[PDB]
Length: 30
Image (cartoon, rainbow, N blue to C red):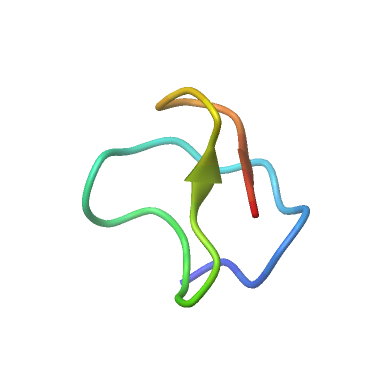
């Protein structure tokens, strides 16, 4: 899982909470 500011891509699995890719689906975690 990606922490934050890490170029990720996905809808469910791609980043790490509480952070998550955004604002779009394939971008960076926030």
